Amino acid sequence: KCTSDQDEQFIPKGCSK
């Protein structure tokens, strides 16, 4: 997930991957 709760400026390792 890219957005988790709310992480608009932050995407984790594996989101767009």
Image: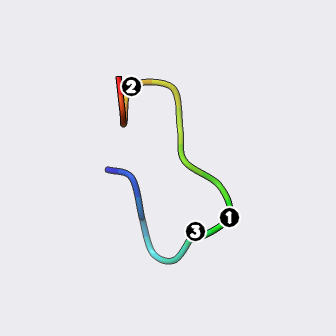
**Residue wearing tag 2:** 14
What is the spatial separation of the Cα atoms under label 3 and label 1, in whole angstroms? Answer: 6 Å
- Local packing at callout 1 (Cα closer than 10 Å; few below 14, some 14-19, many 20+) is few
Which quadrant of the figure has residue 17? Answer: top left
Left or right of residue 9: residue 17: left
Proximity of marks 3 and 1: CB atoms separated by less than 8 Å: yes
Residue located beneath label 3 in the image: 7
User: Percent from the top left, x then y, of residue 15?
Assistant: 36, 36
Q: Secondary structure at mark 2?
A: loop
Eyeballing the image, is 17 above or below 2?
above
Marks 1 and 2, Cα distance to the nearest angstrom? Answer: 15 Å
Count of marks placed on residues:
3
Colouring mode (rainbow / by chain / secondary structure / one colour)? rainbow
**Residue on which disc 1 sits:** 9
Task: Identify the mark nearer the N-term, 2 or 3.
Answer: 3
Q: Is residue 1 above or below residue 16?
A: below
- Which amino acid type is marked by label 1? Gln
Q: Are marks 2 and 3 in contact (CB under 8 Å)?
A: no
Residue type at tag 2: Gly
Q: Is residue 16 left or right of residue 7?
A: left
Residue under the point 39% across and 25% down:
14
Q: Residue at x 52, y 77 (%)?
A: 6
The crowd level at tag 2 (other Cα within 10 Å; few <14, some 14-19, many 20+) is few
Q: Of tags 3 and 1, which is closer to the observer?
A: 1
In the displayed structure image, the side of residue 5 where residue 10 appears, left or right? right
- Residue 16 at x, y = what percent? 36, 33
The amino acid beneath tag 3 is Asp
Q: Residue furthest bottom?
A: 6
